[PDB]
Image (cartoon, rainbow, N blue to C red):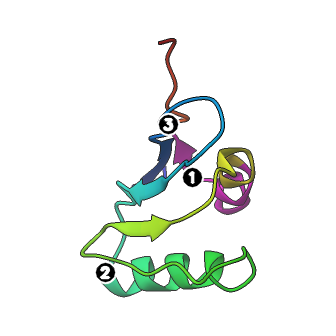
Amino acid sequence: KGDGVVRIQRQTSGRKGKGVCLITGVDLDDAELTKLAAELKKKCGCGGAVKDGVIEIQGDKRDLLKSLLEAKGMKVKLAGGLE
């Protein structure tokens, strides 16, 4: 009962120096995807752009990402791992 899963990952390069955020997987209508990325770029600090299902977001706020995601009631895939 959802049809759509958003997953936010953070490919950092160390402790603190430069982190990136890639948003992809949102299985939803194409026009709907543009509305999602447009909402995050509305009040997140830096207008992020989209790229054929690939929205680039510069910021390590994965925590806030899981929140806005639970706002729609869809599923999420908080990525992670120990390295």
Q: Residue at x 38, y 78 (%)?
A: 50
The image quadrant that residue 3 belongs to is bottom left
Q: Which mark is in front, 1 or 2?
A: 2
Cα distance in 3D space between marks 3 and 2? 20 Å
Compared to 36, does 1 lie above or below? above
Residue 81 lies in magenta, yes or no? Answer: no
User: Which residue is the extreme one toward the left?
Assistant: 52
Disc with the residue nearer the chain's start (1 vs 2): 2
Q: Residue flagged by tag 1: what amino acid is it?
A: Met
Q: Residue flagged by tag 2: what amino acid is it?
A: Asp
Cα distance in 3D space between marks 1 and 3? 10 Å
Q: Which mark is residue 59?
A: none
User: The magenta stretch spans which residues?
Assistant: 67-76
Measured as percent of width and height from the top left, residue 77 is found at 50, 37
Disc with the residue nearer the chain's start (3 vs 2): 2
Measured as percent of width and height from the top left, residue 34 is found at 43, 84
**Other-residue count near label 1 (Cα within 10 Å), few / some / many at <14 / 14–19 / ≥20:** some
Q: Residue at x 55, y 85 (%)?
A: 38
Which residue is labeled 3 in the image? 77
Cα distance in 3D space between marks 1 and 2? 17 Å
Q: Which mark is residue 74?
A: 1
Q: Is residue 4 visible?
A: no
Residue 74 lies in magenta, yes or no? Answer: yes
Q: Which mark is residue 30?
A: 2
Q: Residue flagged by tag 3: what amino acid is it?
A: Lys
| Residue 63 in the figure: left or right of residue 29 | right
Q: Residue at x 50, y 39 (%)?
A: 12
Q: Secondary structure at mark 3?
A: loop
